[PDB]
Image (cartoon, rainbow, N blue to C red; front, side):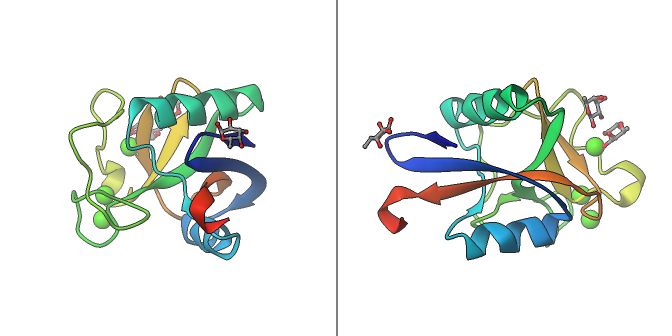
Length: 126
Ligand SMILES: C[C@@H]1O[C@@H](O)[C@@H](O)[C@H](O)[C@@H]1O
Ligand SMILES: C[C@@H]1O[C@@H](O)[C@@H](O)[C@H](O)[C@@H]1O
Ligand SMILES: C[C@@H]1O[C@H](O)[C@@H](O)[C@H](O)[C@@H]1O
Ligand SMILES: [Ca+2]
Ligand SMILES: [Ca+2]
Ligand SMILES: [Ca+2]
């Protein structure tokens, strides 16, 4: 795991679709991880890369309104982002969920893709 002053991050090495990944994180007491700042973002990227992975699902999506991205707590995307160049490109009009790659950058992908995923937990809830 990884643990900051306020959050715990957990990499779950089970291949799931985005929605199953989110429900798994919720049942574990949290949510898909939400990189809202540089510290959290780099921490998640270092974690998945240390585990030998190329990508994981994180908690960002534009499922409800195309092009309106939100975190897994439904709060909106703010000024901070780590989109790779040209992303989010809604490729083939079917990309509504977000992967983080080992560099730390973000790419939108189809939500019916399967991959490992990262949860985040608030320590006041744990
Ligand atoms: C209360 C402390 O909180 C964070 O700073 C962590 O680095 C430690 O593991 C400890 O749990
Ligand atoms: C292989 C494809 O390459 C780019 O178009 C990305 O924007 C897509 O999401 C996908 O990764
Ligand atoms: C590792 C990265 O994964 C993403 O899905 C791709 O879109 C990028 O080109 C890159 O290969
Ligand atoms: Ca869409
Ligand atoms: Ca989209
Ligand atoms: Ca994309």
